[PDB]
Amino acid sequence: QGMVTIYLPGEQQTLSVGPVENVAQLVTQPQLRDRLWWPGALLTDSAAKAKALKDYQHVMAQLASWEAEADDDVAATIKSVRQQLLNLNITGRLPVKLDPDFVRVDENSNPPLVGDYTLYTVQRPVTITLLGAVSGAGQLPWLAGRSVTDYLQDHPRLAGADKNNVMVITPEGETVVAPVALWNKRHVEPPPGSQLWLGFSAHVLPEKYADLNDQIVSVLTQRVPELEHHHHHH
Image (cartoon, rainbow, N blue to C red; front, top):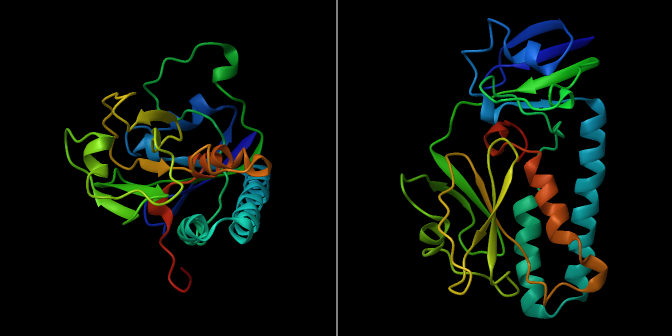
């Protein structure tokens, strides 16, 4: 059965839960259920971390190789994206839905827990994170009612940016496509703590790096930006 080490927000105190048989049992434990901000909670284990690290290093290596081969304007955009991604702390993340209030359909929607796990937690943020081929990347104040296109009014796009869409990645790791052109306009308001990823245009991406947007998104769905708490590294 599963043993879970829980890091409370700030990562300076832990709780221990287990043995637990499955996710539903974990999130309903009396010391957790009504205490944690579940959407931002991040469950992981050694295997998920190892895979995420491999995937991340692959993304960074592709970005470097492409940078060397690209036009100079595109290369400068790639360099910026690379720098935004350089200091991710890779934890991996299991794709389980933690919220106690979710309606679970199908037996497999309550995953068994076997072995050791780590649960990282955060409080609901008051910012969102903007990343990618966009100027002024970083944390932005979250504002009630503001759409993705509203946020982008103050963030010019960089050479080689996707002209059509932003990816919204919620704190749970779910992704929503957010149109940002006139022709495909669709109003989308990202919730507190989301990441907004603006990727590379299909036109600029060479075929050998075709999967690169999806690979980056997959990296981002496995991280919770606030966790980056570190003292002696960036």
